Structure formats: structure tokens, C-alpha cells
Length: 301
Image (tube, rainbow, N blue to C red; front, side, top):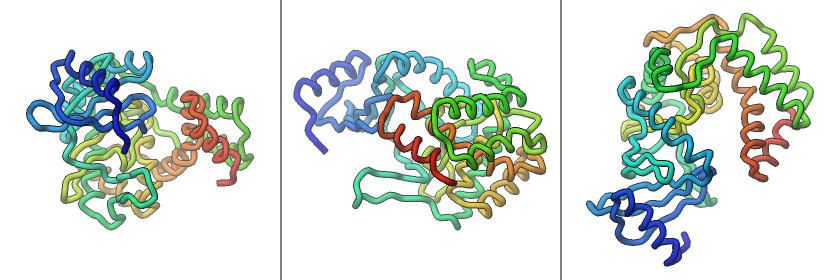
């Protein structure tokens, strides 16, 4: 909501220009991304574009690997993924999306947030169907795209390693810790296969059309081959046990592979989210998100 200075504006115009984007009019800058600065601008044809400018070398270095994943996914999925028209260490850019997400969160107390209704059958069914399609992507295609591949044994070991790391670095509520440990030791819970997963899948990363049907997914930087339950935990979080039960029926009917303790496993994965959050906080360095992580781990569930 503040003006972009003349110097910053010139610099941003020049960045776009060296990639063939001729901007015109005022810029809007969103600084709420940890890894990229976001600039919204109008380009030569009157269409607004999003410029995503990597903030650090480690972010720049992932642009090409992530573009390779997106190119694979575009050709293997029946819904949309991000289409990076410029995909450079310096700049990721694309036309502004016309669809929004199934959860919309805005800064400010008065600004409208939005979340698809619990009782939207169109969303629920299309999400389950889309998720089955993602989990049906051949692992060979993940290999082709340079992705991280975990066997089921590695999947479970990663969880164990993450729990160990959080124990070393944080004070953790005893009952939380014991929950994760019992889960890790419960052979019945764990799948005997892995699949292509999105890895950070919740409603805020699901694009919908004006009928609430899933039209795409975004934020693929954590995608890998791993435990399918990773991609259902946040559905349980937002829509509850009944929402999850419905997801699982539709998912299985659409061809998704399940197992008897899957719903249980998803609940345990959701509880494990506190570990993930804390490790991502620790690695971000961000002081706020870190403080939040510390408080969550210390508190009773």
C-alpha cells in the first residue's frame, strides 16, 4: 500500500526489460514471500504479470530444477500447474492468475479471507479426484524430472530423523513427543509404497474455478516421491474427520491406493506437522515464525 521509489521502480523495469518484458504504469510490490520478492506490473499487452525475484542464491539455484518438475507435471496431470514463462536464476515471471485459491488469506483485520465451504461437494469430489491423479503419476516420471525419491523405508526414516532433530533443537511437550514416537513404532500405520506427492498441499495451494471445482495446484517446491498421506493431512486439518472419510472414499473410487490404517496414519501425519513447521522455521532464520514454532512444540496438543 506504499509507493515504490523511483530508483526501485527503474531497477525493476530494467530487470523485466532484460527478459523481454516491457512494463508500463505503477508497480505493486508484495513483500510477504520469504523466498521471492513479488512485483505485480502491467505489460505491453495490457495484461498484468507477476514477477517473482529470488531473494538468495539458494532460491535462484532451485529455479531450473523446479521448472523441470513443472514441465513434467504439466504433461502428466489433468489440471493446471504454474506456467513460468520466464524461468531464470534472476526472475520467474508469468501472467497474473485469474483463478484464486480454495483458501484466500489476506493481511489486515478488515480484509476478506475466504475458505471453500465444508459442504461444497463439488470441491470435495474434484479435490479427491485430482489428488488420485497426482498420486498416479509414474515414479519413473519423477526420476526423469530429477526429483527426490524415497522408498517407504526412507519415508519412515525421514520422519524419525526429523523428530530427532526437533528434540535436539527444541523444548517439546512430553505427550507430543511420545505421540510421534508411538506412531513411528506402529508398523500397521505405515504404507508399503510411495507415490508422487505435492508435499505442501492444503487449500491455500489449490486453485479453483468459479464453480469451486479444482482447476490447478501451486507451490510445488516440496514435491517428491514419498508417503501418500503427506498430501491429506491438511485436508483433515481444514475439513475434519468426516471430510477426510469422504475424501478417502472418493480417492479410492478414483483409483487411489489405500490401506486399512490410512485414516489413522493421516491423523498422525497431521500431528507431525508441528515438527515440520519447527524445522522449516529453524532453517528460515525468521525470528517470528521461529517463536511461533517454539510455542507450538512446548504446548499441549
